[PDB]
Length: 212
Ligand SMILES: Nc1ncnc2c1ncn2[C@@H]1O[C@H](COP(=O)(O)OP(=O)(O)OP(=O)(O)OP(=O)(O)OP(=O)(O)OC[C@H]2O[C@@H](n3cnc4c(N)ncnc43)[C@H](O)[C@@H]2O)[C@@H](O)[C@H]1O
Ligand SMILES: [Mg+2]
Ligand SMILES: [Zn+2]
Image 1: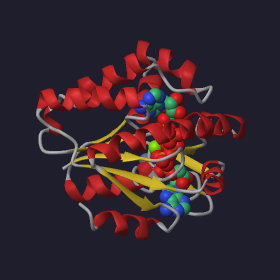
Image 2: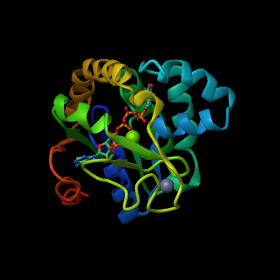
Image 3: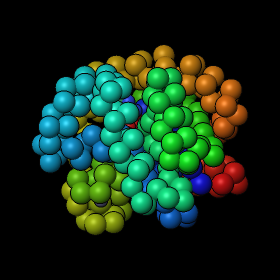
Image 4: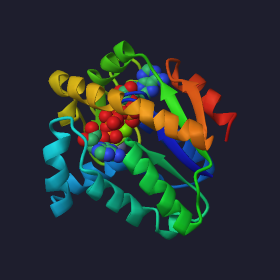
């Protein structure tokens, strides 16, 4: 099961991805999560990406395509994987097509999680993420059982640095204007399937579960 989960910032890609990878036993590959892990370790990669991430802008395709190419080559991606947040530009999608062609692991489905921008904005200014596993929570829509700590490992929850109102605005704009070409690319390939992300976790996962 080779899957790509797309959708604007805050649509629930990570939330749905965790559930999918838990039920299918495949790697959850988030370019955003890989970047932040690189930032925490202070790797040369993290420093480079941080400049763009902090401003809400896209990290250059060269670097982004490069890390995904490497990652998708690992043995854990042999019988499936879930790409989250990649590709988010047509150039990345075309590069991905060739990369998977070479590995012999073409995309099965491209699920787009559709959510109104107003909803997106509220989901981002009330989000808290775990400092050890990256899972996310929402103070209103999906709060941690114990305020301030991750339900799973118990790590402290924090507000992502790029979740500040000003940056949330830039991110939404930056990504909205890239959707049309991406949706057109995948509708053309015939991998595209849309889902109404404006429901409760279970319903969205329910609408997703049926497909897979
Ligand atoms: N391919 C690429 N190319 C170039 N640059 C790249 C790149 N990939 C990454 N980058 C760089 O990295 C940056 C950060 O990347 P990334 O981490 O991928 O940022 P993002 O695109 O902004 O997406 P989000 O993680 O914020 O949202 P999500 O859809 O996963 O939502 P979540 O499930 O947490 O949910 C959000 C909130 O909503 C809540 N929620 C989830 N589902 C529901 C629901 N059904 N109902 C109500 N609330 C819900 C959650 O609890 C949570 O609080 C980018 O801005 C860019 O700079
Ligand atoms: Mg995410
Ligand atoms: Zn955690």
